Length: 134
Ligand code: NA
Ligand code: NA
Ligand code: NA
View (cartoon, rainbow, N blue to C red):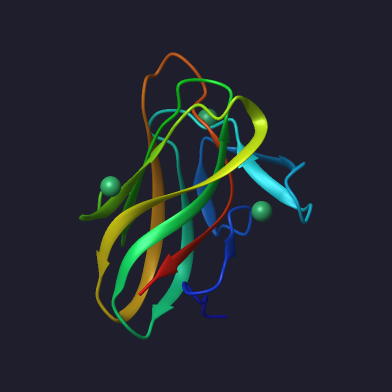
């Protein structure tokens, strides 16, 4: 029941969340995405085990609005920021692109949170999956 950050983790496979909902995705491979994302919402993935330092994250995203950003934190939604990712308008809620951002994560096992940030006035993005790189 550990999660491997160096292979895709599906965003709907969260252990806790605040503010979001899931739906079926039109992205290739099918499956699901999280959506209805607003400024301050988050998702938690428990027991994510890094055997080696991570230096970036890659996230599969879509947005019909101006987008926003994803903060990577551990331990709690307020835990130290380890990196972030900018998410642009992609031309629609099921128009998918992969974005990346730097992180610094040392080996260990963590509760990983993706915390969504942007304007409070519109929903920000959809997320299919994410994966870290060393
Ligand atoms: Na929301
Ligand atoms: Na960044
Ligand atoms: Na997914």
